[PDB]
């Protein structure tokens, strides 16, 4: 039975555009979905897409025989500086399958065991800063969490030291990154983008792109002048299928790609986790009993991090409520029918809105806004395609196990060494630069006086 598709109100030539006049576009689209349900069309001048929210319809869009990965308007604007690297290439470009095969070995169990000692070095530098603050003083949470995650990928991936804890303002690569992502998001809401009114926005965009690339030159110069790491395989590895290596131009696009996607989403996860623990004290208490029982030595081991079983349940429930890269896009390979009721033509686009999928009552029950880590107690026992914070199929996230090992280690050392206080009674305010993070979150931390090691 062929249905007409739902759609919000239109305004002559403007289409649906005056319904997103905001710096928080994903939060606004969540409100249109609660009003119309599992599927709606959305139009702006020149272009069209379709937003999906239920488990039954997202199960079908994830069939790789019928639909593949699409570049959204948002990733087309980022491609202006990340090129044909892993995150912004089409699946049919020569460099996608090639880079994939050449770089996959850097994420194996052997290599993970080899990164552990470098992760502890940055972790110790964070506990030392908080042990040395005076009693009149407080902590800025998302700012210190991005100091730890940028330095950690710098050392493990490239053997370079950004030294972010020897500065009291943010690193200069960070300042230009955050104005570039912001500009790309603002571009999406303009009617006529060519006018002389947007000439200065365009010139500032080029200045932030040159700042990022100046850092790439610096890393290339240090390896030259100087390992079995990510940079090693970029300069020497060969694709077992075609026998080719990567050219110079593609290699620069991969440095930029791994520095940005390799820290920004991990910082965001650690900030939401601490926010939910200080607003739920029966949950905080229990996660602290685990850290004190399991971590009996002066610095943590690789095998001990694997035993921190409840701290992992906490991290997954934080990603269910606020997944830190909150959408991904798809296109139809040939004419087809979706759900048994909506015909589609070769080429039309679809968009998975991840925070709505994670509030489907037919799958999780009627209490979807509560914070309850115990949902994840026997995981093999939750349906397939209900939980997707890392994407789908052959284009899923390559860094999944890296991030989760980093986060479980750092959160357990935080809970062993300090008690925390919500001193300003903080109200949640979520900032959007394509990705998500809580703005202005601040705390106080009192030390339990327990010594560190070497
Ligand atoms: C919890 C933190 C993280 C989250 C939530 C996350 C999420 C994602 C998502 C949603 C995609 C798919 C996007 C799409 O289909 O358009 C993706 C792909 C990717 N991710 Fe992550 N990520 C995280 C951490 C990392 C880390 C630590 C690295 C690197 C060390 C990384 C590197 C990449 C790369 C290179 C791709 C492109 C894969 C390909 O298409 O070949 N991410 N990630
Ligand atoms: C390497 C570059 C970093 C990639 C950062 C972006 C990742 C997540 C993209 C989510 C896009 C959400 C678009 C919302 C706006 C709209 O639909 O109008």
Image (cartoon, rainbow, N blue to C red):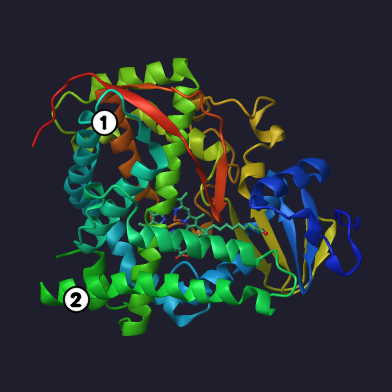
**Residue 297 in picture, x, y percent from top left:** 14, 27
- 293 relative to 141, above or below: above
- SS at mark 2? helix
Query: Is residue 398 found left or right of 438 in the rendered image?
Result: left
Locate ligand 2 by image quadrant.
bottom right
Q: Is residue 377 visible?
A: no
Looking at the image, residue 370 lies above or below residue 243: above
Eyeballing the image, is 306 above or below 206? above
Label 1 environment density (alpha carbons within 10 Å; few <14, some 14–19, many ≥20): many
Q: Residue at x 40, y 66 (%)?
A: 257
Foreground residue, 23 or 44?
Answer: 23
- Which of 438 and 139 lies nearest the eye of the viewer? 139
Mark 2 is surrounded, within 10 Å at the Cα level, by few (under 14), some (14 to 19) or many (20 or more) other residues, namely: few
- How many dots with numbers? 2
The answer to whether any part of residue 169 appears in the image is yes
The residue labelled by disc 1 is 413
Disc 2, disc 1: CB below 8 Å? Answer: no
Q: Which residue is mark 2?
A: 221
Picture quarter containing residue 132? top left
- Looking at the rendered structure, which numbered label has been put on residue 60? none
Picture quadrant where residue 193 is located: bottom right
Which tag is nearer the camera, tag 2 or tag 1?
Answer: 2
* 346 on left or right of 1: left
How far apart are the alpha carbons under marks 2 and 1? 35 Å
Residue 415 sits in which quadrant? top left
- Nearer the observer, 16 or 258: 16
Q: What residue appears at the point 54 percent right and 26 percent down from the top-left corner? A: 371
**Is the residue marked 1 within 8 Å of ligand 1, measured from its CB?**
no
The structure residue drawn at horizontal position 42% and vertical position 32%, both measured from the top left corner, is 442
* Residue 48: image location, x then y, percent: 76, 67
Q: Quadrant of the C terminus?
A: top left
């Amino acid at each position: 039975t062929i249905k007409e598709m739902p759609q919000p109100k239109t305004f002559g030539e403007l289409k649906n555009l005056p319904l997103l006049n905001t710096d928080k576009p994903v939060q606004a689209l969540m409100k249109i979905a609660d009003e119309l349900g599992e599927i709606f069309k959305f139009e702006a001048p020149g272009r069209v897409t379709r937003y999906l929210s239920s488990q039954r319809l997202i199960k079908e869009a994830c069939d790789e025989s019928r639909f593949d990965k699409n570049l959204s308007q948002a990733l087309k604007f980022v491609r202006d500086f990340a090129g044909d690297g892993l995150f912004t290439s089409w699946t049919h470009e020569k460099n996608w399958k090639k880079a994939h095969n050449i770089l996959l070995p850097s994420f194996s169990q052997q290599a993970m065991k080899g990164y552990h000692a470098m992760m502890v070095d940055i972790a110790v530098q964070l506990v030392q800063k908080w042990e040395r603050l005076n009693a009149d003083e407080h902590i800025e949470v998302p700012e210190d969490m991005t100091r730890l995650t940028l330095d950690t990928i710098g050392l493990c991936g490239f053997n370079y030291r950004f030294n972010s804890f020897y500065r009291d303002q943010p690193h200069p690569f960070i300042t230009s990154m955050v104005r570039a992502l912001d500009e790309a998001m603002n571009k999406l809401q303009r009617a006529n983008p060519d006018d002389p009114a947007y000439d200065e926005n365009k010139r500032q965009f080029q200045e932030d792109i040159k700042v990022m690339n100046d850092l790439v030159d610096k890393i290339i110069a240090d390896r030259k002048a100087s390992s079995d790491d990510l940079l090693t395989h970029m300069l020497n590895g060969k694709d077992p299928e075609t026998g080719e290596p990567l050219d110079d131009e593609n290699i620069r696009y991969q440095i930029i790609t791994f520095l940005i996607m390799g820290h920004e989403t991990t910082s965001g996860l650690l900030s939401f986790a601490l926010y939910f623990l200080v607003k739920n004290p029966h949950v905080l208490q229990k996660a602290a009993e685990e850290a004190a029982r399991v971590l009996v030595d002066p610095v943590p081991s690789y095998k001990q991090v694997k035993q921190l079983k409840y701290v992992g349940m906490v991290l997954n429930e934080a990603l269910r409520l606020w997944p830190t890269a909150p959408a991904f896009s798809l296109y139809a390979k040939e004419d087809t029918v979706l759900g048994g009721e909506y015909p589609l033509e070769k080429g039309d686009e679809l968009m998975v809105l991840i925070p709505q999928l994670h509030r489907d009552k037919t799958i999780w029950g009627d209490d979807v806004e509560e914070f309850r880590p115990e949902r994840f107690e026997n995981p093999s026992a939750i349906p397939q395609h209900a939980f997707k914070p890392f994407g789908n199929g052959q284009r899923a996230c390559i860094g999944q196990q890296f991030a989760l090992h980093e986060a479980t280690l750092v959160l357990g050392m935080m809970l062993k060494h300090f008690d925390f206080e919500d001193h300003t009674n903080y109200e949640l305010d979520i900032k959007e630069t394509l990705t998500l993070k809580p703005e202005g979150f601040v705390v106080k931390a009192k030390s339990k006086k327990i010594p560190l090691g070497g």
